[PDB]
Image: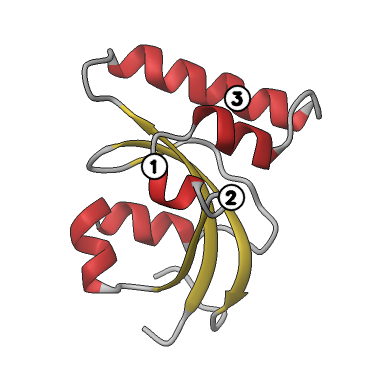
């Protein structure tokens, strides 16, 4: 709840597309990032369906863990998964209420915690 992470993302909407074709592209985008054929910022501009964050180079700003407003839009699983990642990670595709996200954690201020 005081844990905060700053994140950028590439959002892959599934509106009027097949979920499988969308996830396949997201996985391939990620592999092209890994092999340095494209950068994260390049992938954001070319592929992200989130116009508002795309206009900020993908930046969503700071999210607090369990933030209700962020939990309500994208789901508790999305918020929870972002906080599973460490600063500088670019994530595997994350499912949410709207489609799939490739997330980069650009900043992180959070207490270490066990898994129960």
Give the labeled residue for mark 3: 29
Considering every residue shown, the one lying at the far bottom of the view is 2
Considering every residue shown, the one lying at the far right of the view is 36
Q: Which mark is residue 61?
A: none
Q: Are marks 3 and 1 in contact (CB under 8 Å)?
A: no
Q: Residue at x 26, y 59 (%)?
A: 76
Left or right of 53 in this view: 85: right
Instruction: Report crowding for label 1: few under 14, some 14 to 19, many 20 or more residues within 10 A (C-alpha).
Output: some
Name the image quarter holding residue 110: bottom right
Q: Nearer the viewer, mark 2 or mark 3?
A: 2
Of pointers 2 and 3, the one earlier in the residue sequence: 3
How far, Cα to Cα, is label 2 from label 3? 16 Å
How far, Cα to Cα, is label 3 from label 1? 16 Å
Give the labeled residue for mark 2: 57
Residue 1: x %, y % from top left: 36, 83
Q: Residue at x 47, y 16 (%)?
A: 24
How far, Cα to Cα, is label 1 from label 2? 11 Å
Instruction: Report crowding for label 3: few under 14, some 14 to 19, many 20 or more residues within 10 A (C-alpha).
Output: many
Of pointers 1 and 2, the one earlier in the residue sequence: 1
Q: Residue at x 21, y 16 (%)?
A: 16
Left or right of 69 in this view: 37: right
Give the labeled residue for mark 1: 50
């Amino acid at each position: 709840l005081p844990d905060i992470s700053r994140v950028s993302h590439i959002f892959f909407s599934t509106k009027d597309k097949k979920r499988s074709d969308v996830l396949d592209q997201a996985k391939n985008i990620l592999s092209q990032i890994r092999s340095k054929k494209i950068t994260f910022e390049e992938a954001v501009r070319k592929y992200s369906n989130d116009e508002s964050s795309k206009a900020k180079n993908g930046d969503l700003g700071f999210l607090s863990r369990g933030d209700q407003n962020a939990q309500n839009l994208l789901g508790a699983d999305f918020v929870k998964e972002v906080f599973n990642f460490n600063k500088g990670d670019i994530s595997s595709p994350i499912a949410s209420k709207e489609g799939f996200h490739i997330v980069k954690v650009t900043e992180k201020y959070a207490r270490p915690h066990r898994d129960a």
